[PDB]
Amino acid sequence: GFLGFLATAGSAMGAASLTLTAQSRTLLAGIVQQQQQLLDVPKRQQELLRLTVWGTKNLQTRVTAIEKYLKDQAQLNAWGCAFRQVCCTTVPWPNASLIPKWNNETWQEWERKVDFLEENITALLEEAQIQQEKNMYELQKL
Amino acid sequence: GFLGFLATAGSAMGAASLTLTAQSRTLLAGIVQQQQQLLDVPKRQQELLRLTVWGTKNLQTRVTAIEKYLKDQAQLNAWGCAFRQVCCTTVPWPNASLIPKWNNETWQEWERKVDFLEENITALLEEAQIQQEKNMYELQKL
Amino acid sequence: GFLGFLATAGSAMGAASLTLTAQSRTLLAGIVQQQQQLLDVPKRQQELLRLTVWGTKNLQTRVTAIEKYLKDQAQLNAWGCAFRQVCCTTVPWPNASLIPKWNNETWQEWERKVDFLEENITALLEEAQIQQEKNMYELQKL
Amino acid sequence: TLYVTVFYGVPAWRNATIPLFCATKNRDTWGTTQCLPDNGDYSEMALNVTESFDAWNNTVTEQAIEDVWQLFETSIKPCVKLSPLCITMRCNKSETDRWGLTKSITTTASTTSTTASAKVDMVNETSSCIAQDNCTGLEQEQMISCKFNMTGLKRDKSKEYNETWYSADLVCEQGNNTGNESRCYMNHCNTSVIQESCDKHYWDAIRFRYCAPPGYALLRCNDTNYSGFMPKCSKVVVSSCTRMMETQTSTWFGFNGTRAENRTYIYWHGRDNRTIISLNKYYNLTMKCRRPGNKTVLPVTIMSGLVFHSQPINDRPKQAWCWFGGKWKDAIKEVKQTIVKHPRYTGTNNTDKINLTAPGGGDPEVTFMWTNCRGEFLYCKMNWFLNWVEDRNTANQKPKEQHKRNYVPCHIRQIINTWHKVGKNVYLPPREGDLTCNSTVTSLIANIDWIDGNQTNITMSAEVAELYRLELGDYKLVEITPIGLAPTSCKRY
Amino acid sequence: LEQEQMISCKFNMTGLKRDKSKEYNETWYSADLVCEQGNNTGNESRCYMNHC
Ligand SMILES: *[C@@H]1O[C@H](CO)[C@@H](O[C@@H]2O[C@H](CO)[C@@H](O[C@@H]3O[C@H](CO[C@H]4O[C@H](CO[C@H]5O[C@H](CO)[C@@H](O)[C@H](O)[C@@H]5O)[C@@H](O)[C@H](O[C@H]5O[C@H](CO)[C@@H](O)[C@H](O)[C@@H]5O[C@H]5O[C@H](CO)[C@@H](O)[C@H](O)[C@@H]5O)[C@@H]4O)[C@@H](O)[C@H](O[C@H]4O[C@H](CO)[C@@H](O)[C@H](O)[C@@H]4O)[C@@H]3O)[C@H](O)[C@H]2NC(C)=O)[C@H](O)[C@H]1NC(C)=O
Ligand SMILES: *[C@@H]1O[C@H](CO)[C@@H](O[C@@H]2O[C@H](CO)[C@@H](O[C@@H]3O[C@H](CO[C@H]4O[C@H](CO)[C@@H](O)[C@H](O)[C@@H]4O)[C@@H](O)[C@H](O[C@H]4O[C@H](CO)[C@@H](O)[C@H](O)[C@@H]4O[C@H]4O[C@H](CO)[C@@H](O)[C@H](O)[C@@H]4O[C@H]4O[C@H](CO)[C@@H](O)[C@H](O)[C@@H]4O)[C@@H]3O)[C@H](O)[C@H]2NC(C)=O)[C@H](O)[C@H]1NC(C)=O
Ligand SMILES: *[C@@H]1O[C@H](CO)[C@@H](O[C@@H]2O[C@H](CO)[C@@H](O[C@@H]3O[C@H](CO[C@H]4O[C@H](CO)[C@@H](O)[C@H](O)[C@@H]4O)[C@@H](O)[C@H](O)[C@@H]3O)[C@H](O)[C@H]2NC(C)=O)[C@H](O)[C@H]1NC(C)=O
Ligand SMILES: *[C@@H]1O[C@H](CO)[C@@H](O[C@@H]2O[C@H](CO)[C@@H](O[C@@H]3O[C@H](CO)[C@@H](O)[C@H](O)[C@@H]3O)[C@H](O)[C@H]2NC(C)=O)[C@H](O)[C@H]1NC(C)=O
Ligand SMILES: *[C@@H]1O[C@H](CO[C@@H]2O[C@@H](C)[C@@H](O)[C@@H](O)[C@@H]2O)[C@@H](O[C@@H]2O[C@H](CO)[C@@H](O)[C@H](O)[C@H]2NC(C)=O)[C@H](O)[C@H]1NC(C)=O
Ligand SMILES: *[C@@H]1O[C@H](CO[C@@H]2O[C@@H](C)[C@@H](O)[C@@H](O)[C@@H]2O)[C@@H](O[C@@H]2O[C@H](CO)[C@@H](O)[C@H](O)[C@H]2NC(C)=O)[C@H](O)[C@H]1NC(C)=O
Ligand SMILES: *[C@@H]1O[C@H](CO[C@@H]2O[C@@H](C)[C@@H](O)[C@@H](O)[C@@H]2O)[C@@H](O[C@@H]2O[C@H](CO)[C@@H](O)[C@H](O)[C@H]2NC(C)=O)[C@H](O)[C@H]1NC(C)=O
Ligand SMILES: *[C@@H]1O[C@H](CO)[C@@H](O[C@@H]2O[C@H](CO)[C@@H](O)[C@H](O)[C@H]2NC(C)=O)[C@H](O)[C@H]1NC(C)=O
Ligand SMILES: *[C@@H]1O[C@H](CO)[C@@H](O)[C@H](O)[C@H]1NC(C)=O
Ligand SMILES: *[C@@H]1O[C@H](CO)[C@@H](O)[C@H](O)[C@H]1NC(C)=O
Ligand SMILES: *[C@@H]1O[C@H](CO)[C@@H](O)[C@H](O)[C@H]1NC(C)=O
Ligand SMILES: *[C@@H]1O[C@H](CO)[C@@H](O)[C@H](O)[C@H]1NC(C)=O
Ligand SMILES: *[C@@H]1O[C@H](CO)[C@@H](O)[C@H](O)[C@H]1NC(C)=O
Ligand SMILES: *[C@@H]1O[C@H](CO)[C@@H](O)[C@H](O)[C@H]1NC(C)=O
Ligand SMILES: *[C@@H]1O[C@H](CO)[C@@H](O)[C@H](O)[C@H]1NC(C)=O
Ligand SMILES: *[C@@H]1O[C@H](CO)[C@@H](O)[C@H](O)[C@H]1NC(C)=O
Ligand SMILES: *[C@@H]1O[C@H](CO)[C@@H](O)[C@H](O)[C@H]1NC(C)=O
Ligand SMILES: *[C@@H]1O[C@H](CO)[C@@H](O)[C@H](O)[C@H]1NC(C)=O
Ligand SMILES: *[C@@H]1O[C@H](CO)[C@@H](O)[C@H](O)[C@H]1NC(C)=O
Ligand SMILES: *[C@@H]1O[C@H](CO)[C@@H](O)[C@H](O)[C@H]1NC(C)=O
Ligand SMILES: *[C@@H]1O[C@H](CO)[C@@H](O)[C@H](O)[C@H]1NC(C)=O
Ligand SMILES: *[C@@H]1O[C@H](CO)[C@@H](O)[C@H](O)[C@H]1NC(C)=O
Ligand SMILES: *[C@@H]1O[C@H](CO)[C@@H](O)[C@H](O)[C@H]1NC(C)=O
Ligand SMILES: *[C@@H]1O[C@H](CO)[C@@H](O)[C@H](O)[C@H]1NC(C)=O
């Protein structure tokens, strides 16, 4: 992709600039170019496809891109908010001592100040999604 | 890891805490440990990464971790559940002779009594979705 | 080997299918058969698992199929129609000069007449999604 | 009314047959290359479930056996082949005749001696007989000095070398040598090619644990009644990784086991009478092996450019030998009692009618005990030991076997047929200096075989692989399959 | 139909004992040999494999 996603960096957290489409287009551009090379290599070298170091390396970089995509989509589905921007989860923020300055701090600066909250939050967000869905089951039965 | 799937085992069919999100996090754990080891091996061995049996066993488990994740998401999609806590269906249960005791039997005991139906049910659930897609298409034409 | 898509290929654009679940079924059949063989190869041959070229060809084949599956899902997520049939985007059709005959042409015939539009359309659909996304961000913020 | 509904996150599983990951702490060679680091998590949780366990028909034990074997093979694979050494060597005749590799009829020996000569000899740490390697009954090692012509990388030049072989490693041509310099070849060269185990294999301990991949879990029996085969195990413990395993391969007795407990357990194969008897650690049973003498090691570069480690000792050291300490007499009494009370045993309840015994035949892989002492294999004849621990009335075992001692004579063999089901021959490089090993004794490998209510024969066995079923064995691997179906009234919308 | 055309050749080959060797009886099909030509007025012609 063009990596235009990070172009806004330095703009401050509240300066909009968030997007849900940037990773799909980066991955899609990647897949087309990588598949073309997988099919291009055999025009000169058909035996040594992963029998060499470069073969193994190309495997590793194609797989890494896929694993990364799945890690993020899987986590969002766990929280349920795959297409919801802000997502609106019901888990309260841990404490008042860690509040962002939306018109001063950037997302890079902010995220590095809350790395230890993500460790407790991920689990809370997942449970909130489970509780909401089991309540819907009871409502459908009623 | 966590094994919340086993932690609630023995609680009966009228179970609490069906930790749906557990599959997403088990995928993440898999990716992280295997990726770190693959990055570590080249420190001493850069050539024989997949070319010695240990690396064919480790590649197989990495590719499989991706495939197992996808088999479940794909089966769930095949049955109409983008997200499945219970994701109710339109397919009736095969017969009244096989009804669980929600307050006595466990999921381990129950599932091992209905493996027979799972093979016939999987197909029925998929057929129900096919008809639902056809119905949506007719509504789109209208 | 469900062949659900090809089955309606000879009809008309304004006539049949628009099936989503068939891709999941195809992937599931593929993964299961590959897994059964991968479990089977070690029953007789454990050393030559990725070392020789036949195993790299089977690996590239599997990786390409996984990337393809995810490629379509990623494109749909960008457009939002992961599960929306017709999607309903807001980008105008490029010109009134190229119009389908819903009751005479098939999708195969039609798609081969818009290959030179897709190049501009994919980008336009993504741009439209981006502006809509920005508008939704501000509405959610308010 | 009732629709199938599908529940996700369901706490249920089925039998898995997949590869496990190895994880270790020793990352000097094979660890960095093949294994995950040891996560260090040894915790477990219990479930209120019943499950069926079987040590022999297990995938966990099956992988332990096969993986230890394969890591051995991938270590020796790139080492120097010794086919260039399968040439006639010129060996000292006195030595090849003296230790039976060649024949002579000119020795015309005649011996008259007292037959009422059996002795009892005990040794312990506080003794000069150990420090000086001279206990009653210990003879010389039997090393044979041979010369041979070998070529290095210069090709058109060659040198003569001094190699001293153990007698167990040579064949030696027989008949009509009326002079000196007998003609010898390596014991297992001609039907095959001997490869050197050059990458320090067996020079240190190999320990690792297995970890389940995501979506899989290990279940374990936490009973005291687990006897290898148990249809309904009521105490089932859940974990993600196994206990740490010691991949040690010795016959008759297992050493350095992880399953060291203040209890005697006997696993019986459910379909057979082959068993693994653990020993009660209470008695601090230990084996101390010594290989006397200061060895010199001389690297030789041969043709391909790879190096072979020769042994130009030019000396006559005492035999390698092993000393047994700890309360052996009492540990054995417990084994016999444990067998008597065991649920699969219907033999004699008289502990004076239950005996340990060697397997018969002339086959050294079962009649001896093979201990890997830091890289050198040490086969030990154990009649003195067995007579002692049993307090056996020897009487008619012939004069050198009638003694009761807590130590046994042993010999070093460098060309070792490997333990797995391959039949492959490898060469074990010598260790420089002397060798001493102090190991714990944790298990006995034996069959229990009785046909009546008198004479039960605990027959020592050489199937080294059985030991892995004591190290693990109580583990079962299962797949988590968290999709359930169950009729309910809640039809979609 | 005629005879197959097989040629009986002897040679000295060494096995794993290296300093010991044996002579072997090998019968080749005629198309598998080259054979050196000129002034053999006796017996034992000198041949090599066709593609070595
Ligand atoms: C997950 O993993 C676990 C752990 O491995 C799995 O658990 C194991 O699953 C196995 C497969 O089902 C079980 O083995 C089978 O047991 C059957 C029943 O055996 C008993 O009955 C035999 C005959 O009795 C008949 O009549 C009675 C009337 O009351 C009926 O009730 C019976 O059902 C029968 O119809 C009897 O002969 C058996 O005794 C012999 O075997 C047991 C084995 O434990 C020994 O302990 C005994 O000493 C005795 O052994 C002698 O005889 C056998 C030959 O039979 C020789 O080999 C021995 O050396 C010795 O001389 C039991 O009392 C068996 O019928 C069945 O055999 C049939 O099927 C196999 C193919 O699978 C054929 O090869 C056979 O020839 C035969 O047709 C088999 O042995 C394990 O017991 C069970 N393990 C545990 C700990 O529970 C679990 O299934 C896995 N789950 C999944 C989903 O994969
Ligand atoms: C059952 O279990 C018991 C344990 O309960 C086992 O017994 C123990 O086994 C240990 C592993 O073999 C052994 O440890 C070795 O002892 C050697 C002797 O060292 C003595 O002094 C040191 C202090 O300096 C003490 O710590 C030690 O306990 C002894 O008293 C040491 O030499 C070994 O150290 C080596 O390995 C480390 C690895 O990090 C190296 O840094 C170090 O330099 C040594 O390296 C040599 O060996 C390695 C093997 O990996 C080679 O790769 C390396 O190149 C070196 O080898 C060269 O040097 C030697 C001469 O030094 C030469 O002969 C050779 O040809 C090479 O040139 C290590 O510390 C325990 O002492 C031992 N304990 C007891 C009480 O017995 C028992 O084996 C198990 N039994 C069974 C049945 O398997
Ligand atoms: C770790 O394992 C040890 C064994 O290896 C355990 O030690 C054993 O503990 C039991 C239970 O207390 C003792 O059994 C008692 O022994 C006395 C003494 O009887 C003696 O004389 C009779 C003949 O009259 C003879 O048959 C016996 O063998 C003795 O020589 C009896 O009076 C009692 O009724 C009972 O049988 C064992 O004797 C003792 N063994 C040893 C070697 O000391 C130890 O308890 C275990 N540790 C833990 C923490 O569980
Ligand atoms: C381990 O060895 C013991 C001792 O040989 C075996 O015990 C034997 O068990 C078999 C049955 O598995 C007995 O055969 C049956 O005996 C009954 C009663 O006489 C008879 O009615 C049957 O027709 C049949 O002959 C056998 O007698 C018994 N022998 C003794 C001396 O107890 C044991 O089975 C062996 N374990 C395995 C799995 O091989
Ligand atoms: C590999 O060598 C063994 C032994 O070598 C021969 O016998 C020794 C006693 C000695 O005289 C050497 O110089 C000889 O070369 C061969 O095994 C012998 O085979 C014969 C014939 O079947 C049998 O009578 C002997 O008892 C066997 N001796 C032993 C010790 O096993 C073996 O056949 C050779 N293998 C190959 C492929 O050549
Ligand atoms: C061992 O058990 C016997 C009883 O069982 C007999 O011997 C077994 C080895 C086996 O062959 C069975 O089938 C036999 O039936 C005990 O014998 C009894 O001892 C008491 C005294 O304590 C005596 O009054 C009884 O009459 C004896 N019974 C018989 C049938 O003789 C024997 O004492 C036990 N020995 C040990 C060490 O436990
Ligand atoms: C491999 O050998 C062939 C043939 O061997 C030579 O010619 C035979 C008739 C016989 O006399 C053998 O002993 C000889 O060694 C070589 O082919 C010949 O090449 C020359 C030169 O180009 C040509 O004039 C001949 O006609 C060829 N003869 C045949 C039968 O093809 C060939 O060149 C050798 N290859 C190499 C690399 O040495
Ligand atoms: C194994 O145990 C023996 C004792 O049986 C140890 O040998 C002693 O080592 C000390 C320290 O170097 C010396 O002072 C003693 O003289 C030695 N005893 C004898 C009989 O020689 C030995 O060091 C221990 N382990 C190893 C690996 O060698
Ligand atoms: C970065 O600096 C340029 C001036 O060089 C300015 O125009 C731009 O808006 C700044 N970007 C951000 C995110 O503040
Ligand atoms: C409370 O705020 C402080 C501010 O630095 C932070 O270190 C701490 O972890 C917070 N407590 C939580 C999340 O419970
Ligand atoms: C498991 O057993 C314990 C007692 O050891 C009991 O308190 C608990 O409720 C039991 N749980 C289940 C699910 O049966
Ligand atoms: C009907 O019930 C019986 C149990 O009595 C079961 O074996 C059978 O598979 C069931 N059939 C269907 C279609 O569910
Ligand atoms: C569970 O078993 C009890 C008898 O112990 C019975 O009364 C009850 O109705 C059963 N529960 C269900 C859901 O069938
Ligand atoms: C599945 O359907 C087939 C008919 O296609 C029937 O014979 C079989 O018994 C059914 N299985 C179950 C468990 O009802
Ligand atoms: C395809 O041809 C068959 C006859 O072979 C005919 O029955 C069917 O209606 C045709 N389908 C279409 C879409 O024209
Ligand atoms: C206009 O229509 C022609 C004819 O179908 C086509 O070739 C051309 O690409 C179209 N232009 C645009 C902007 O779509
Ligand atoms: C299909 O072709 C017929 C002429 O055969 C024409 O009348 C009809 O309008 C065409 N259908 C469409 C959708 O253009
Ligand atoms: C296993 O058994 C021991 C007693 O021998 C007990 O202390 C331990 O807690 C048990 N482990 C589990 C996970 O229950
Ligand atoms: C061995 O090599 C030496 C030279 O280093 C040479 O003098 C001697 O004759 C050789 N012996 C044999 C048997 O080839
Ligand atoms: C030794 O010599 C005798 C003749 O004196 C002969 O019969 C015998 O076969 C010879 N043995 C060997 C091994 O050469
Ligand atoms: C022993 O070897 C020497 C050569 O070093 C030779 O001269 C002598 O004759 C040999 N001994 C016998 C009995 O042949
Ligand atoms: C070849 O066979 C003949 C018999 O036709 C035999 O006399 C001769 O010794 C054999 N030669 C070899 C090298 O085996
Ligand atoms: C054969 O002999 C003649 C002399 O009579 C000589 O000129 C010719 O070169 C020889 N040919 C071969 C192949 O030796
Ligand atoms: C055939 O070979 C023998 C040697 O085995 C030799 O004596 C004889 O002279 C040869 N024949 C001819 C015609 O030269």
Image (spheres, coloured by chain):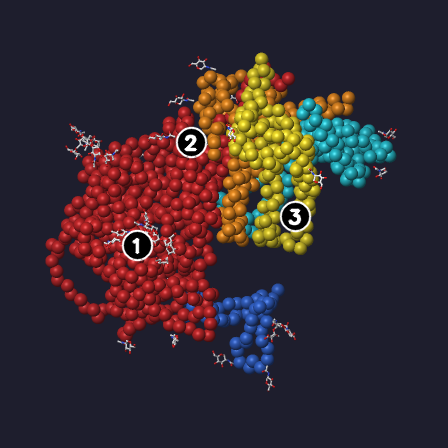
Chain colours: A yellow, B orange, C cyan, D red, E blue
Quote the CA–CA distance across marks 2 and 1: 40 Å
Q: Is residue D414 left or right of residue D112?
A: right
Q: Which mark is residue A103?
A: none
Q: Which mark is residue D238?
A: 2
Labels 2 and 1: the sequence-earlier one: 2
Q: Is residue B86 visible?
A: no
**Position of A63 relative to A132 (above/below):** below
Asked whether D111 or D117 is in front, the reply is D117
Chain on which label 2 sits: D
The spot of residue D68 in percent (x, y) is: 41, 47
- For label 1, the residue is D378
Quote the CA–CA distance across marks 1 and 3: 55 Å
Instruction: Locate residue B71: give its quadrant.
Output: top right
Quote the CA–CA distance across marks 3 and 2: 43 Å
**Position of D142 relative to B86 (above/below):** below
Mark 1 vs 3: CB contact within 8 A:
no
Residue type (three-letter) at the residue carrying disc 2: Val
Residue type (three-letter) at the residue carrying disc 1: Leu
The spot of residue B45 in percent (x, y) is: 51, 52
Q: Is residue D493 left or right of residue D458?
A: right
Q: Which is closer to the viewer, label 2 or label 1?
A: 2
Q: Secondary structure at mark 3?
A: helix
Q: Is residue D357 visible?
A: yes
Q: Secondary structure at mark 2?
A: strand
Q: Which mark is residue A38?
A: 3
Chain on which label 3 sits: A
Instruction: Locate residue D301: give its quadrant.
Output: bottom left
The spot of residue D50 in percent (x, y) is: 40, 27
